[PDB]
Length: 502
Ligand SMILES: *C(=O)[C@](NC(=O)[C@H](C(=O)O)c1ccsc1)(OC)[C@@H]1N[C@@H](C(=O)O)C(C)(C)S1
Image (cartoon, rainbow, N blue to C red; front, top):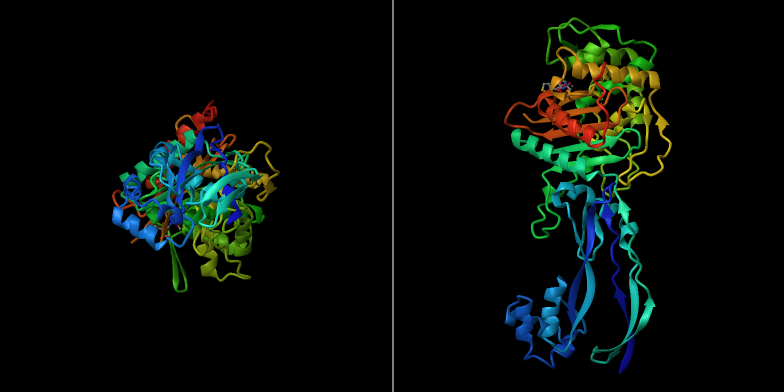
């Protein structure tokens, strides 16, 4: 006859900003319309105007009400503007009710779609930060007591038994200015090279903060009608790859820490191949005999790094890679984040020793690679990763000795600045450091990973471009130019003083 029931009071989802307070996700007030069929059934002459207001066929609308004439609740539509919300309310139909709800808008849209993420139809987080910090952002909902009659007509609002608590504001580590630069330059590299996909990550080597994370393809998270799923992949965090030659500096770190190698030591790489039973190690350029350790990185000799790997043992290389976080949990607690794999064999045969040392037989993400380079640039100290603005920097872990990291930094500066090096990664006005890669998946992954300024490193960056088709595929020519252009702008946006001085 008269029954007490409780209706959920939706809560306003917390504002997401970039590190500078620019809005990235905002809760917009929407109006949801529900109906009591049992009441609607007493006012059928109003139905047609309501169907039209909801853009529905009059017969399909009517059929649906009749089919649910037993129920006391149905959604009519979720998530109208309050202006179109009022339109339907004006129609004054018995048994139509309104709930005030919230809809996310993403001001920056596709520029930061993967990082910021997406909410489902219930305003819960579903991809990216929205998912990872859903508990922070969501906000516990409210409860109001209503009286209903036996037909389920809402007679009376009685009281609020639990206040809605709004979700909490969250400032990302992302800098929208760098995020826009990275986005623009990665899109243009994708189109210039007719490539299938790519990622670019920018990290603060001192604070562990991710300043930019971008992927192609991307999508407009404000356009909830397409949802092409391949464009929704946050590739920087969920696509694993063999990193190939971008891990040679970690091989070189193991070599320098072994006590068996100094930078001026020499390896004979002639004739640019080496038989390992069934396997044959090949250098792309084979006009070399004696190379020093720096030369082995400038020419990316697989023969040279392999011979060093045989001398020092796979264990020492595995150890460095594990300590800098290759194939390791990032601690970011993004659900569905990929960890890849760094297989720890007890002893390694020669084949597996060589392939590890030049970046096959492990799987990593662009974010792990960027983090690893961050530790190398930060004098061998790994600072924990963050996707949220860091006020108080947590203690880092010394994973490579400062002398060794300093020495390898210098070698990577030579990889960029030396005769026959990756000149396309040069950053006019600054000393930049890094290493190119070109990985087989004929299908190629183009890689460049590095940091700047070499004098006092601030920024680590990774560029991954999947299946370039138009103009070659070497990391040194496809990805290096992107690193150059994004590092040119990012350093200046952060007011990092040019270090290419007397
Ligand atoms: C590292 O990435 C690199 N890559 C290769 O040797 C490739 C392979 O595995 O066959 C490759 C050779 C020709 S095209 C792809 O060594 C494991 C070397 N580093 C690359 C780079 O710096 O971009 C080279 C110079 C292409 S070879």
